[PDB]
Amino acid sequence: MVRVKICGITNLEDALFSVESGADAVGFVFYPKSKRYISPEDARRISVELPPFVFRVGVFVNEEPEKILDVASYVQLNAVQLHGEEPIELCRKIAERILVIKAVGVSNERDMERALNYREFPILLDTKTPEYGGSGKTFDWSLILPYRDRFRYLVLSGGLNPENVRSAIDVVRPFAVDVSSGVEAFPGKKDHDSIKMFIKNAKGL
Amino acid sequence: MVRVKICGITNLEDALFSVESGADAVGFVFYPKSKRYISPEDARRISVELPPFVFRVGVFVNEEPEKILDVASYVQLNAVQLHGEEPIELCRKIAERILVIKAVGVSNERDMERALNYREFPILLDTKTPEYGGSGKTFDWSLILPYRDRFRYLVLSGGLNPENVRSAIDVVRPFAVDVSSGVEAFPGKKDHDSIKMFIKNAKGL
């Protein structure tokens, strides 16, 4: 069965609803220019309130290493998602202290070739970018297939929503699936019926 | 749906099988006198290999605080399970840095009253002790019921096995369920068919 991360959580109620509906991880965006940004202090409040067995992931975009580690210990993150153009050296330094997921933008196979240099880390494939946080009237999920067994663990991301998750999962059969705006009411606020349906469809409940 | 932690993991293959069968957390026992003991070094090897979105919990029994924190950062644990007679002060100090689950032995309601002093932390109720790591031709799960809503998150433990999990869960409706010997081939080695059935029955798959 697939794991599900709900990203862009900005408030306690959305986080708790996610956990109770079956989400395995919640994500906090620590990138200042994001509309889904949450301060380490606001995030800490939420993290501390959440139950065990649910990953708290912090999203950073080209943040300097020392700051990433300080926010992680403060907010008590379980993993760091490096979503910029961080070099493997930076990734390897962070990995000495906390688990790192390297996010890579992907739109064609040259991007998948770039992704293969990071194969030592769990990879989050952020499909069809920039545009927004993801999206497409279904990205050709099959183009990722020939590279699937080259990675240890794969998290599918970008444009996933309640109507298209199952298809994406059937094709790729990833370890996890990730979503932010595909289950939003508006920027920073989740739509509960959407989170419910997304998890039900992704997991086959 | 309930979360499932498989405790007493001593080897990589048992851990990976647990994750792939649906377990949400794996537990490493760092109590030297346990037959399921694993050194921080051996545990680190396994932790580093596991995918994200799966909790690594470390089990300590009356260990001094500084040593608990060192093993946690070294092995990259996501939570600490204090399974001795640790006072709330020790629990509160550890909690400043990493999530803590307080395990409490429970056989009657005086024990549940003792458990209520730790209600600020997620509680693991270790039913019917000492004897072994748990057990009973079903502990009267219903005695925990009147105390259920006093705790934030509850992890049911002790004597759970593939045949009795559903019943225990129906009665209490805990956040999680925990098992070690109920899915073992012998001390330290898991039986894969048992892990499979336990998770399938606990989660209703």
Image (cartoon, coloured by chain):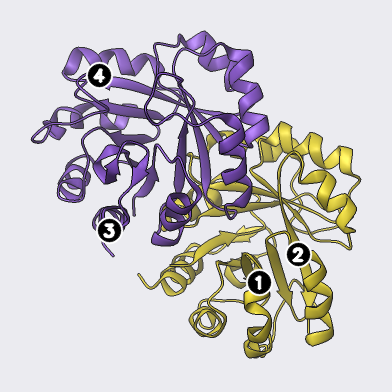
Chain colours: A yellow, B purple
Left or right of A169 on screen, residue A74 = right
Q: Are marks 2 and 1 in contact (CB under 8 Å)?
A: yes
Label 4 and label 2: CA atoms lie apart by 45 Å
Left or right: B37 as drawn, with respect to A171: left
Q: Do marks 2 and 1 share a chain?
A: yes
Residue B14 position (above or below residue B32): below
Decide if residue B96 is in sight here. no
Per the image, the residue denoted by label 1 is: A157
Q: Distance between the residues labelled 3 and 2?
A: 35 Å
Asked whether residue B40 appears in the rendered view, the answer is yes
Percent x, y of residue A192:
49, 62
Q: Is mark 1 on a helix, strand or loop?
A: strand
Query: What amino acid does circle 3 point to?
Result: Asp
Disc 3: which residue: B193
Report the chain holding disc 2.
A
Q: What's the residue type where badge 1 is placed?
A: Ser
Res A103 label: 2
Q: Which of marks 2 and 1 is nearer the N terminus?
A: 2
| Along the line of sight, the residue nearer the viewer: B188 or A180 | B188
| Residue contact between numbered discs 1 and 3, judged by CB atoms under 8 Å | no
Of the residues under marks 3 and 4, which one precedes in the sequence?
Answer: 4
Q: Is residue B49 above or below residue A150?
A: above
Q: Residue at x 54, y 50 (%)?
A: A15
Q: Are marks 1 and 3 on the same chain?
A: no
Task: Please tell me the numbered disc located at residue B44.
Answer: none
Instruction: Residue under label 4, please give it.
Output: B112
Tell me which amino acid carries mark 4: Met
Q: Do the residues labelled 3 and 2 touch (CB within 8 Å)?
A: no
**Percent of width and height locating residue B41:** 61, 33
* Same-subunit check for callouts 3 and 4: yes
Report helix, strand or loop for mark 2: strand
